[PDB]
Image (tube, rainbow, N blue to C red; front, side):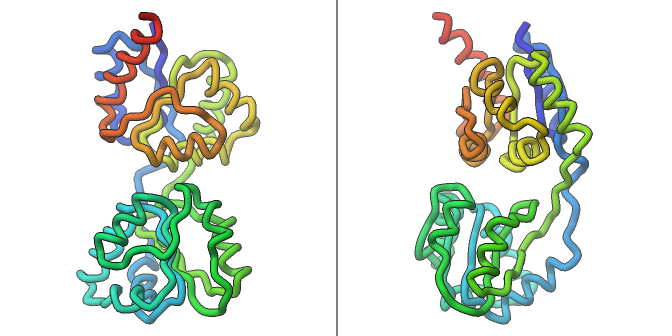
Length: 254
């Protein structure tokens, strides 16, 4: 039977039940330590943004929407400050959310944070950066290097599980997994950033192990780390991912 590993923490029960119903042999290898944890300083972080920024960088569509809602609930005017700032979006999702909010981006990257480096302006002031659970040293440091005071905007903080990341990498290189499902891009990132041999990992996921991604953003993370997704669930539902995956497997043999 096809051994399908799950890197989420979230829906382990649903995954197990789903995989079995399909005749798959379910494996659980989480890469996150625990549930999303609140960031103390967030509220003050949003108040800071309300004071005015020269540059605003958005990484996700959900992130922009949640930030804007938080601002309106706190009685803060965020649309004003962002209206006079240079707005950059990492990719299409972030761009659309900004667009729909009446604050279209001035430039958009290719879905990867690294693509924003070249697009950063030259000036001194404050650069607000909407995050999705983890720090982005490369981008943050690029912003500071450009002369901006980086203002991280992260509502929740995700925890990687070193121990679990290594067990997952061990398993993959050892050939105990046939497919690996990632429900979120941060899971792909925690895995490669915590791995001891990312290239053996990349190699495994490009030949012996089929990488499955829930959502285009999760897929973007796999491609960014040099992995070609075997299957991408555009409907963002774990159930559809496994159903569609089982269909893809059969079609390869048909």
